[PDB]
Length: 207
Length: 207
Image (cartoon, rainbow over all chains, first blue to last red; front, side):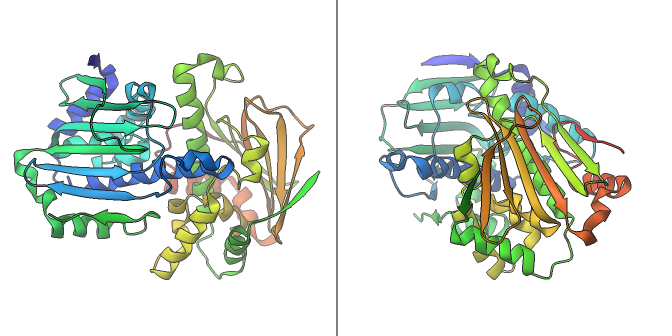
């Protein structure tokens, strides 16, 4: 279990998302589903020239799993996954520059819902989650677990849990007042509203 | 000079873009600039762990170059570029599946301006160009030139022209009735309207 400090800029981004009064929290799902779609495109592209890339799972999909008992909403995809280096490097993003662009945009009249245009949509998860746990498996590495409750630090460790073949699992440990996102009708409404055209099957699990 | 046939689906996409009556042609710029931004993010990400990736050019930018003499509008970026394999594989996209998703969306009420959501925004270039020439240089390959006037085929050849260091250049040979896109005020208007938040400097060259 290794503990790392977020780069100053990412810490800033997270505190902004956590402290700014902003009612349109539901966009977090759109952002995470969009990220999953991007990850699926990546593994698909690689398989175009190397079919064995899919040996770890040919199905390219996205699952939305609510769990009222654990108060978690999990977004699972069978995309390219992330290596340990990717996790450390801001979950495979260029978050430092992306954050700068996002800040400048906000200054120019943009709002938080536009976060995905700057490649840092993952962090919108903190609009509804007190802690985010990311389990991932990339073809070229072992299975790892990234985790953070913000506060300037994140941890990374090899995951000894359920082997996932290939992909990423974003486990949102919801804030006490954000349990509406565990309700079937609410999730379904949000998916139809913002992710109706996603090119991969989205399956909303029931309890 | 090798000549290749577009996959059936891509040929279909191109004919739809070329034959469908659709007045909102200006979105082509937004799509190409968005693609350039994506390519710049990729090289930036690679440099995070390997600084030498930028030996071929540290500047990450986008240039818009109108040329009334040649009737061309060129979008140049210093992104990751494309290998010969990338060019052949639909300019580094997963166009076959992307096209399917785009078609289904169109059936579901979406319109052509939403093409970028399906990863095939490059082809919107045919809304205004009779022929598109793409010059590219990736760190791991030589400089190549891809070209197509649609009609079901494209060509690829090693480019012996001006060495570009690293990146991609999309040369739009405009249709005779689309010369408004060579005008400074028009290009500027389109950039402000659709690409005002792009996180890389966009320079509109003058003549």
